[PDB]
Length: 262
Length: 15
Length: 103
Ligand SMILES: *[C@@H]1O[C@H](CO)[C@@H](O)[C@H](O)[C@H]1NC(C)=O
Image (cartoon, rainbow over all chains, first blue to last red; front, side):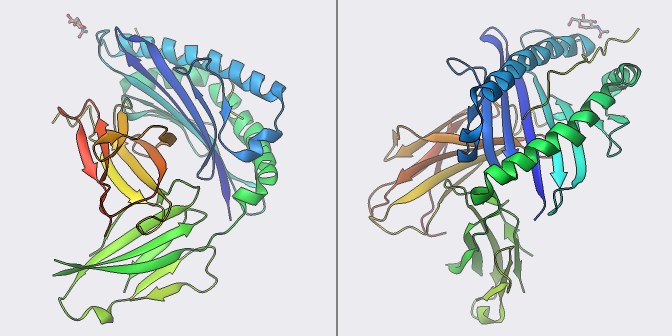
């Protein structure tokens, strides 16, 4: 199983209601492990996974000081962006940043990611080479030139290849009981008079990656079920009495043999 | 472990 | 219908286990593909606010739209109605979505 660490950082302005709200959420694969929220009483990073009880007070203090500095970087860059786009104060605006690393099943680095969005569309993103930038509009073309001159990409590349990978290795080991487990899906089919709708359900599985096929198709994005497992359904509309010709297939890391059901 | 504080601002005013 | 600057939430309401009356379970309200990120989510039991709902799994997708899970432990009965009520700037009125037990 390959693994990833990813952070999701968002600031959103709320003019006349106070300063922008800053939130940072960290994930290993699809497990949330830390979270900062500027609207909490006593904003700090807090653990959301049991393996993060291993880290000491120095770890929490240092990443909470990063969040306090990062909050101000998002608030000033929101205010810069209003002037770049000649926008009035008073409108709601959003700055997003997603970044992280992917490793193979042997732990070696597969790729890194740094991507920014203003008001929910691309702004600037670092290419797969971890060296050059893709600017999505006229403002981002100016940032790209300034960031090429300042060598921004070198600071991100050092993080993505070093710190990001080294912490992801530490979290996979400290949380191996949660993160390296395999919970195989429990599947069933439901029958809905309509035509007729056949719905193949997969419940109780871990990790989230799955394939559901009917042998066209309604489905939902794989979704968290509230206790750290995932679920998914896929449906087909079939002819009103000949539904035993149809077969639901499920592929998962915990099924050496895929399930077949009807 | 998150990324450190972003070193550079967007600076998208132009001339 | 300012579809260039807002995205309307998709609201999915589902249990961890197939429901059995008087068997303990978890009810989820996964609120997805919305923008901007400010949102308010209540889980309702017979039309009233369930206290102590956990909010978790805040993320955003490759198209930058926002995702968040609300979840609570509950024991379904034959006569308890459960719903998720959402307020978001994309929508004039709070939207209430009823749990479909038999999906
Ligand atoms: C920027 O906005 C102001 C105030 O809304 C407007 O009067 C002005 O013409 C705009 N400038 C440009 C370059 O569009």
